[PDB]
Amino acid sequence: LTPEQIIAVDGAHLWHPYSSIGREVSPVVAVAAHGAWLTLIRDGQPIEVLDAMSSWWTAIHGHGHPALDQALTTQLRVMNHVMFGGLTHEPAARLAKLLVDITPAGLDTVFFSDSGSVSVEVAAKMALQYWRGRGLPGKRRLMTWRGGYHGDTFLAMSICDPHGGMHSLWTDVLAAQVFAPQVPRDYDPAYSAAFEAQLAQHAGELAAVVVEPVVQGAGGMRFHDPRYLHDLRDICRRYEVLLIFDEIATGFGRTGALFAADHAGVSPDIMCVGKALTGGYLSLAATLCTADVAHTISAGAAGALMHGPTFMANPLACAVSVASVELLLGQDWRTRITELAAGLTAGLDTARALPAVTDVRVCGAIGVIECDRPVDLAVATPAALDRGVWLRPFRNLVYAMPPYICTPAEITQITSAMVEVARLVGS
Amino acid sequence: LTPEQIIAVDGAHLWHPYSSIGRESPVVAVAAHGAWLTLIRDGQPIEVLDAMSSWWTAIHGHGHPALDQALTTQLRVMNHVMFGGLTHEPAARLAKLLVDITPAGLDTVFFSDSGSVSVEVAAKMALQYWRGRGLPGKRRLMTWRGGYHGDTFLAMSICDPHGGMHSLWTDVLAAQVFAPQVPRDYDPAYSAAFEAQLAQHAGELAAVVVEPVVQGAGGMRFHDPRYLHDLRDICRRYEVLLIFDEIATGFGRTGALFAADHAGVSPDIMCVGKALTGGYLSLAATLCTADVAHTISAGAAGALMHGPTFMANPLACAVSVASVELLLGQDWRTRITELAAGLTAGLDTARALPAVTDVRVCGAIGVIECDRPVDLAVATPAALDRGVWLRPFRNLVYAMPPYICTPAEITQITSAMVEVARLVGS
Ligand SMILES: *Cc1c(COP(=O)(O)O)cnc(C)c1O
Ligand SMILES: *Cc1c(COP(=O)(O)O)cnc(C)c1O
Ligand SMILES: C[C@H](N)C(=O)CCCCCC(=O)O
Ligand SMILES: C[C@H](N)C(=O)CCCCCC(=O)O
């Protein structure tokens, strides 16, 4: 199909995410991706632009990395997929061993699934089944703080920010969960004391606290002091409420630590990972839990964990994930991310002086220009493309989560485009 | 890793589906090619038939050269890009194929990453539809018993609450409306009763959701396609949407391209998955009519706020395009008829077995139903001894073999199935 043909079929038959159909955006045709770069069709002509978004925060080693391509083709040659019901295999074993070794201590059990939203559903199921296994089925609600996002399936939606979150129109049909106020950027003991007070009054009906550690992504690219996670861990411990960290966006080095929990030295009872898990090649996610959680879940009268995605532990997805994680661990990723952060900080600093900019902030390989108004994609997208960068703002944010392989020059091209988008926003 | 090292790691760290940890032992798989798996039995690698098609996905068998090549072709040009703001050739080629081969009127495609997600998307579409019509009270689902629709919490709510796999969770799930178990043979009184029950709930129902013709994970039950014609009629007259979940029945499995085709009926919304990718990669899709898509988009809500990270993944779409074209490029209907005949002929003798209550076949689906639960500890090694990978569940010994299975291979599969049933009764 020609780009023309692709656009026609697309307009007629494809529903895009977070969109209407008809009077929708109008997507740009992508025809190739290599390293940090996408080949897009603009006015009938192919242009090369930097994938500043890492393809929604997944392509940490860039596209078509030789190690990941090879890992995929090697597995393809021997075994594409077998059912995980009754069978196991090397890629599943290798990936699970890697995951339990690099995640916060105590997470020794791995349940694979096909997507981040599903892994969150699995996390909640683990938490609820845990308490059923202890003969306390009243412990069935979740608690979180505002500003959060945990995916788009219906249980996941129930812990999305109920007022400004993308799922706010659904609140009347969602499970009603417990929400603490927005966690602040700077550490304030009074906030943690209030969180504890609120949790204490609901402790008998709470299965778990569920939060994104350090960085809240889709809810506003907000950062908070890691010490709050230390307080959550302690509160949950004392009141016997499970602690769940959703690291689907923060995992695999993105915030400057291997996992954002590591900024706090905290181990949750349950953890979700996804997105950058496969290096952005294929859909895969995982839910990890402690031995105590795993063993209790089938205690009393609860029985087996009745979850089993058809493509659970897919050998192809697991094999590229093994390669992606090994590639990350086999380099000095900590210095790499530090250099990326310094580059983002340096390149975004001029945005602070722009009239429509309210904040500039960087955490690891995350760079954010917060604006005083919602960012118009119709203006932003071509402005970024004109400067050789693929950017997709959302809410009032011009942000990047670039591939780890970006050179300092490429980072400066990305930040330059961001600043120019923000400049255009304010005029 | 060696097989023993894999077993060690697996036992320590891997949670398997529908199981407990440290109380459930998996067999190591080291290769798969065509209709055969290479498994490790007592230290020896053996080749056995994938009678389950790896949970009903591997319709062209494993490592089919056309599908392998499609994947490797796409890998060299573009592994993945975000579907937010971008589009691409594999998504367009796949959407065009699916719109063309599905029941008439299904012209919009929302891709997702798994069957259960595609079901939640379908439900979201149905609820958002009625909101766009100013009827937000229409928010419950109706289905019939014996059904299965996945494992996420909304999907669980339309699993049969009495004896379906999610039955222990009834007290926490959304309470949906359940009609009685639909019978095998057509009885118009069943439809009239379904209508009567639906009528009293019509003002609060967004949709009827069912598996058409074959109910899979809820018990491998078959029903007359005329029931689906009745549901189309009832939904039309009472203004309730009709959703067909064809995640198990799609792509030829029941003898028609989609099971809905047996009834000559189109749902308003349709889910597909599993065999969509030929069993290579996780992918699913939710299709809807122009009416549904436009009504959603014209509502105050506006956008459908759903967007899986790996939505319309190029690699998954590329292998699916190849799998679908490979199916359409051959006489699949004759192939399935031949498979059905082979299954019928090979399972016939099981009818006489003392613990067997029914034998039934529908397209490339063969079922022995027993009078008691089937013990995997007896069934699994028995079948492996006969060169077949079988996974019974509940009281069912069944197969959903790759379409490429030879008559000899089908003979081998059915013989193992008969032998497992024989052992159940002793
Ligand atoms: C397998 C299946 C699903 C869910 O698929 P997963 O990939 O396991 O989420 C949903 N509905 C039906 C009818 C199925 O057979
Ligand atoms: C992206 C994301 C999810 C869910 O991801 P999908 O892959 O879209 O299902 C969940 N939680 C967080 C924090 C995320 O960033
Ligand atoms: C796509 C995935 N579900 C995700 O969490 C990222 C969404 C956050 C950005 C919203 C947008 O780009 O429109
Ligand atoms: C979601 C799951 N893979 C599925 O729907 C098919 C499995 C149903 C059979 C249940 C078993 O084999 O134990």
Image (spheres, coloured by chain):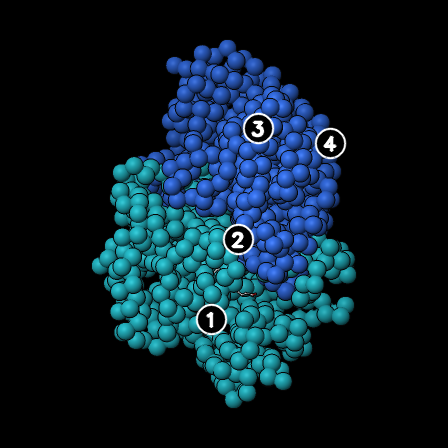
Chain colours: A cyan, B blue
Looking at the image, residue A94 lies above or below residue A103: above
Where is mark 4, residue-wise?
B331
Whole-number angstrom distance, CA of label 1 to CA of label 2: 23 Å
**How far apart are labels 4 and 1 at the CA level?**
53 Å
The residue under the point 38% across, 37% down is B168
Does label 2 lie on the same chain as label 1? yes
User: How far is the residue under mark 4 from the one under mark 3?
Assistant: 40 Å
> In front: A266, or A143?
A143
Q: Position of residue A205 (x, y in %)?
A: 30, 52
CA gap between label 1 and label 3 equals 53 Å
Residue A76 in sight: no
Is disc 3 in contact with disc 2, using a CB cutoff of under 8 Å? Answer: no
Name above or below for residue A141 compared with residue A425. above
Q: What residue would you read off at disc 1?
A: A221
Which x, y percent locates residue B41? 42, 31
First in residue order: circle 4 vs circle 3 = 3
Q: Are marks 4 and 3 on the same chain?
A: yes
Residue at the image position 62 percent from the left and 74 percent from the top: A376
* Pointers 4 and 1 within a single chain: no
Q: Position of residue A45 (x, y in %)?
A: 75, 69
Q: Position of residue B166 (x, y in %)?
A: 42, 38
Check the residue under mark 2 and report the chain it is in.
Answer: A
Mark 2 CB lies closer than 8 A to ligand 2: yes
How packed mark 3 is, by other alpha carbons closer than 10 Å (few <14, some 14-19, many 20 or more), is: few
Q: Identity of the amino acid at label 4?
A: Asp
Q: Which mark is residue A283?
A: 2
- Taking depth in this image into account, of A268 and A196 the one nearest to the observer is A196
Q: Earlier in the sequence, mark 1 or mark 2?
A: 1
Count the labels in the image: 4
Residue B305 position by quadrant: bottom right
Please rate how many residues cluster around mark 2, counting C-alpha atoms within 10 Å: few if below 14, some from 14 to 19, many from 20: many
